[PDB]
View (tube, helix red, strand yellow):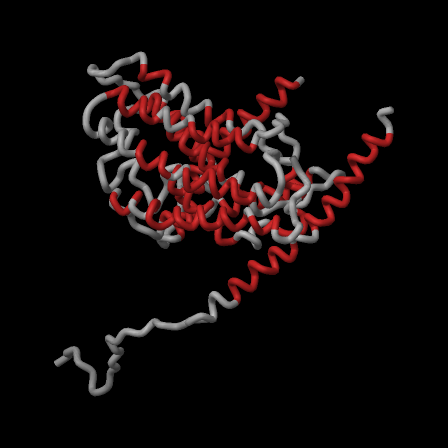
Length: 318
Length: 67
């Protein structure tokens, strides 16, 4: 029945990414002093069944000027590498056990931006043309900030797999010891996935609407359901790579219970920001990475290398 | 002969500006901070120095049998 363990995953998650869109504007509602979608629910909890159905009734135009062969294979992705990445992710028991799999995320973190470059180019001119070009450029310069500061800690835990990374955070919430890094693990995923303070990719201010501009109701649910299938995953990751829970070979169930009451707090962070801060004006946006974020990330790497060796600490792995 | 201004008495309420309160300033931070980071590593160097002590124990059974 291994095929019914899968399809029990893909389906029950599409409800979260659906019902996030509701808690989008309730939480961001009371920052403003008001209430959130209310009239339709009664509580509102019934809103997203009505919204999923307005789009696919609503007619899906294509530009007369487009290349239809690319205008499909691209979105036929924004929903794969979002739903594949979930596969080897322990909670506690991952569906797959990949030997070195931690590295496998970067494989699928790196291969999504090659679905932006298609779509914005697939269609047409300068609002999605050079406007989907220069959100490529920022999306690849926030990896080098990443793979390093992912690679740092992994000196402090011994291997590439995720079954060890529950063992080492036992009674030490891995955020003490590298708290300088942890910050930069946060501003990255918020800068890379195109969210609030570095917002430019999806346009509001700097342009009209980035990269979404062409898709009518028909395809544009996918992206608007793809872009929220990354955001609740990196943030359902960070908390396996920092704030660890305590496995329990007996009541596995109490592992996940206490696990979603963390990863679900953590997420409610990209909403708790977006009410707050303004945007960066694309110069300042990269111009603050090389100069500023990076020099440290190298420097710390020269540090977490020696700290095990200089304490006879060296973590028990191959 | 019903008009507005009261007989006497008012505020004012000021227009002034103050909202500066801290908050562990001026090197008080960099003091607690570097103090936590250490107790992080001291919490390592022991777990990680214990876990190896089990590591050898595990490779022991392998060599024990396998004649």
